[PDB]
Amino acid sequence: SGTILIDLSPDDKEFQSVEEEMQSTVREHRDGGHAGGIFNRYNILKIQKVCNKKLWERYTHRRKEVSEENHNHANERMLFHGSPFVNAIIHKGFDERHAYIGGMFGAGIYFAENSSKSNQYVYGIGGGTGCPVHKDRSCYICHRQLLFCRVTLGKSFLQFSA
Amino acid sequence: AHSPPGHHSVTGRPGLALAEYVIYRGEQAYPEYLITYQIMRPE
Ligand SMILES: [Zn+2]
Image 1 (cartoon, rainbow over the protein chains, first blue to last red):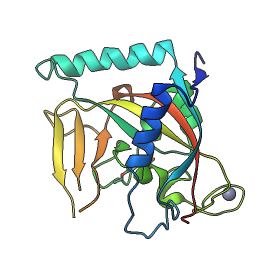
Image 2: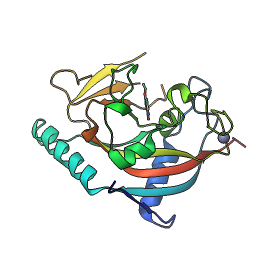
Image 3: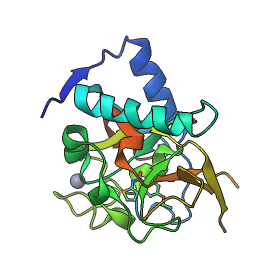
Image 4: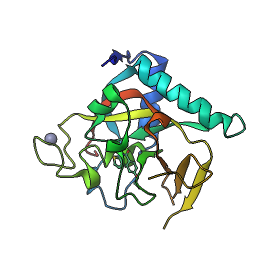
């Protein structure tokens, strides 16, 4: 694969700034927690740095291309991604298989500023049938995973919604 | 699908909601941090 996961200490400034982004970007959802569950905050169990040489160089190569098409501006963000396929993503990277075909904004890969938005997709679209163990979209027991991703936006098409 | 011509991404502009983003090429994202968590039942 080439992927290693490095555990961050809770004492590490990097752990604390990622936790704060996770906690501070929770909002209430219009489904009243149907898809992602009822909560105002998370119990953070672990934060791991994802290290893959090939996938990083794949990222930085594409970033330079976008940047050079956009007056030397990658327009790079740190955004949340929720998916049942997080394990495939950390090992093989994002591809066509991670696209949301039925997405409001077209068939592409979706990212959120709201951690609680990405949380709605960890067990699938609309939270699917919830956690595999309890069949509960609002399960307080089962361990969930989100990706906090470096995303090159370049020139972004502004779509107004609702 | 592809980006709208002359663009690299889509911004889904949201009262309290923050933005959602769409990229059409997987190379335009790197998964930096894997976060393991539980949602917490409110008090
Ligand atoms: Zn469960």
